[PDB]
Length: 6
Length: 6
Length: 228
Length: 228
Ligand SMILES: N=C(N)c1cc(-c2ccccc2)c(CNC(=O)c2cccc3c2OCC3)s1
Ligand SMILES: N=C(N)c1cc(-c2ccccc2)c(CNC(=O)c2cccc3c2OCC3)s1
Ligand SMILES: N=C(N)c1cc(-c2ccccc2)c(CNC(=O)c2cccc3c2OCC3)s1
Ligand SMILES: N=C(N)c1cc(-c2ccccc2)c(CNC(=O)c2cccc3c2OCC3)s1
Ligand SMILES: [Cl-]
Ligand SMILES: [Cl-]
Image (cartoon, rainbow over the protein chains, first blue to last red):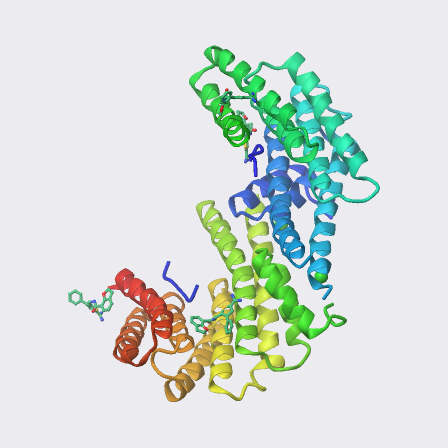
């Protein structure tokens, strides 16, 4: 899964 | 703190 | 529910709840603060975002576990419980979208506040899209795209390329393209141009802002490494 | 609340909730299963314990954060919010104790089940004691001691010294002595004699039971290392 703004 | 049965 | 508590006390308690890792409480306190009807400061917007991001994050993680188990099964219990979690998640998303629409976005004149809220709107329609399947998946997806797009337009006009809200917006819109809209090339293109334009602007920043901006650039880099 | 759901479906959903790290749901499902009125299996007792241990664990961790902030402060908001968390924690403890008293303990004939439930009773009075200050702290403490003591008496008579429930009971009673009852020498004595008598019984065990027992012995060792 890609990173979104944590 | 001491360990209790997690 | 929070109607009888002072706005300042709600904010104070949201910060305590964060320290205690009590994110459902944090979100309820910030919902109460929003419903006082006054605009939110930068710090207060971040408290709102942190609270609901953590609440919905737990729900999304649970939904993915259950959906995977459900898929592997190709009784009604797994479906029932996945539906229970899904309905709770949708309720949280609906609550956040309701706060943005009543009336955070319309009262946000500044680019910093308006972009922040429109990014949030995109994010919470995106979370609705992750679980959507009915007659409304396409409309949900287009609602996310529209919000993200308006935020992008304002941020490109009004903010420098290293602004952390602009960077986090571009990161999440890129994830939308890749994961939701089945547009991996758009996702890659957006991540790369955002990364490169931030790099070229780092020379203008203090040591502190430099650290702030490079932190989010690292997440753009991580996705490009996953995708290319 | 769970009255309309089949017992087997509640158990199934408790296991799903555990996999999804949804411990409040897990606890509600297991409360519903208990309230069906049938005894609980070994596996089902563990599901009950895991669920409420995780729920109350989050509450205790939050309470400690807030109590420390409150102490450092020597407005009413910190106290109010600590009280809110405390009341929620007490409610969870009261619910568990109510399940044990209505009617898990009275229907538990076997040593394995009766010791398990009496250990739980000691544990949840201990959690009440951690936050107690009123006219009832001493009575709460003595309720914990009494439950632990009855469990110890049965476990010493009916279980081998390496039994994991017996070991976990002794571990927690030792923590009670050290942290709650201001009896650190009793705590150290209990941990040491439990550790030594388990060591002397390991030769009777399979590789699997050996791993089970040594895992809890390691926690007894860790506390002795902290305390001596
Ligand atoms: N309580 C919390 N968890 C937070 C409170 C504040 C806060 C904001 C303003 C004033 C005081 C505190 C947070 C910052 N939020 C961001 O998005 C952010 C991310 C990266 C870099 C920067 C950012 O802002 C300025 C520079 S996070
Ligand atoms: N579809 C595209 N846009 C790309 C095709 C290729 C490519 C790869 C191999 C051979 C030929 C082309 C790319 C090379 N990666 C980058 O430039 C890049 C830039 C910034 C940050 C990161 C990057 O990679 C991981 C992290 S990006
Ligand atoms: N769902 C869960 N989290 C659990 C399900 C079961 C379970 C129990 C019986 C049958 C099937 C599963 C658990 C085990 N519980 C213990 O206390 C325990 C601890 C250490 C060693 C042993 C133990 O039991 C047998 C040996 S934990
Ligand atoms: N009050 C006591 N009962 C002790 C006094 C001393 C002592 C220390 C220094 C000098 C003289 C005496 C003890 C030594 N530790 C143990 O035996 C022990 C046994 C099992 C496991 C562990 C142990 O330690 C940490 C982990 S225990
Ligand atoms: Cl359900
Ligand atoms: Cl409160």
